[PDB]
Image: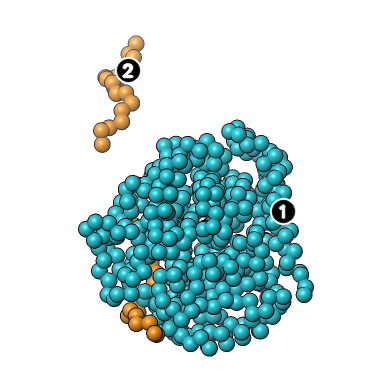
Chain colours: A cyan, B orange
Amino acid sequence: MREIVHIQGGQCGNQIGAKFWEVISDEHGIDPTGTYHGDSDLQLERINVYYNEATGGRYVPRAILMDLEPGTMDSVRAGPFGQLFRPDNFVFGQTGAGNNWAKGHYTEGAELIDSVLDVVRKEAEGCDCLQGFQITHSLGGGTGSGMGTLLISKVREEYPDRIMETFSVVPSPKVSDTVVEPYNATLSVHQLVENADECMVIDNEALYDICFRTLKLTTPTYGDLNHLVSAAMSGVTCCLRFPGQLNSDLRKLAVNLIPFPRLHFFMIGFAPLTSRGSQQYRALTVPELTQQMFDAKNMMCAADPRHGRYLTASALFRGRMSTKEVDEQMLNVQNKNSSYFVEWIPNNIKSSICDIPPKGLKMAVTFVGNSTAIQEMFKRVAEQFTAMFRRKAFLHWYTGEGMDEMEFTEAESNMNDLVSEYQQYQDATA
Amino acid sequence: LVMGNNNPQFTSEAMSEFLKKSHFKLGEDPSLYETTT
Ligand SMILES: Nc1nc2c(ncn2[C@@H]2O[C@H](COP(=O)(O)OP(=O)(O)O)[C@@H](O)[C@H]2O)c(=O)[nH]1
């Protein structure tokens, strides 16, 4: 009943999903053996969105774990909450991609992806009425960035009217992990802009900055980063699972946030986030939540929104609060920051209220914003890519198994066209 | 002539027989259900 399936790809995607499912199970009161031990009735009335019913009274997540090397999935199967997943849903290759977009999209993706399409079909149309798909992956890794986007293409072709959502991790050069990042990042962006309905960008640099500054903890870990990402993911779809004053689902959010068909790259942030020592020095109130929400540093991207203009903004509030206060705060912010809001879109913030807060918290907010500042990421990635591609560095590895330089030229042209089109509306006047 | 005194040596080269994982975050408050309606 308007449920959404989960497909995670690559090492990064598997690490994201292994924590997201733990967070969801904790929220819904599902034990690691799959037996419900909750405290109220509201925890089971919409449990069908993310889970399936099996014999014996246990629940199984409707997730599909696909990858090219079995090491990551063997690691996540032995961890806590690793017994929930159906062992059939594990699909793996034998050779891997080796951080090669060409290998992950042409030479092993074509051979393997048939089985994962079969399992995606089974899980998706075994449902009552599908709501959409959500994907977690990173654009810096070969197998993920290629096979996941080919999966996006085929799934979109087979389901043209469904909602497609992706949580993308964009590689930053300040903290770089792969010397071949620009190539596969550009190719993935080109293949994604044509198909994906919604895309969100996450940056490990911004995650490190948040963990060091706000939480004020000495040594962050990928567990902590995955925890922030999982909280952000659950915040978006909480309203689809719990009753609220103003209900709003993924399709509503997309319709209200996407002005033009090709502008679907958002950035997200979460609030409140306070350190342990100063956790109770603050007071949970709507003005404090909204100021920490609209704080530029709190955003999960290195793209500074103060360098551009917000096309639209979205705020999903969790808890019990007064709609008059929420609307007054939104109007006050939109009036006090008139410069950063493009003028031909009056009242350009959407608001929502959900009565069930995250566990352990009384008030929490999920923010999704589309601002003209993300073009800096595209410009920098294109600059690095063209610098590398001028001298034909690392080109033979990609061209040895099917591609030609014409597709790279087309990717550059499309990427620059996207940049120009997206910066066009920044200086537009009414 | 006397060659030397060191009687045997006879020894070659020989080699003798001889948790981050989890996360640290989150603050807890008592659960508050029962929506407004
Ligand atoms: N947020 C987050 N990012 C990760 C994690 N593990 C890896 N990454 C990022 O993923 C990138 C490498 O991805 P990769 O392992 O090559 O993906 P794959 O090729 O699909 O397996 C690196 O730049 C990391 O920053 C994680 O647990 N959390």
The label on residue A111 is none
| Vertical relation: B19 (above or below) A66 | below
Dot 2: few (<14), some (14–19), or many (≥20) neighbours within 10 Å? few
Dot 1: few (<14), some (14–19), or many (≥20) neighbours within 10 Å? some
Label 1 to label 2: alpha-carbon separation: 85 Å
Residue A186 position, x and y percent, is 63, 49
Q: Is mark 2 on a helix, strand or loop?
A: loop
Q: Is residue A423 left or right of residue A69?
A: right
What residue is pinned by disc 2? B4
**Residue at x 77% of width, y 73% of height:** A429
Instruction: Residue lying at the far left in this picture: please name it.
Output: A56
What residue is pinned by disc 1? A416
Residue A100 position, x and y percent, is 55, 41
Type of the residue with mark 2: Gly
**Residue at x 22% of width, y 58% of height:** A56
**Residue at x 34% of width, y 82% of height:** B34
Q: Nearer the viewer, residue A204 or A30?
A: A30
Within the image, what quadrant is residue A375 found in? bottom right
Question: On the same chain: label 1 and label 2?
Answer: no
Residue A59 position, x and y percent, is 29, 60
Within the image, what quadrant is residue A379 found in? bottom right
Foreground mark, 1 or 2, reads: 1
Please, which chain is the residue tagged with disc 1 on?
A
Residue A45 position, x and y percent, is 33, 71
| Vertical relation: A2 (above or below) A315 | above
The quadrant of the picture occupied by the N terminus of chain A is bottom left
Instruction: Residue lying at the far top in this picture: please name it.
Output: B1
Q: Is residue A37 left or right of residue A328?
A: left
Can see residue A272?
Answer: no
| Vertical relation: A326 (above or below) A73 | below
Q: Is mark 1 on a helix, strand or loop?
A: helix
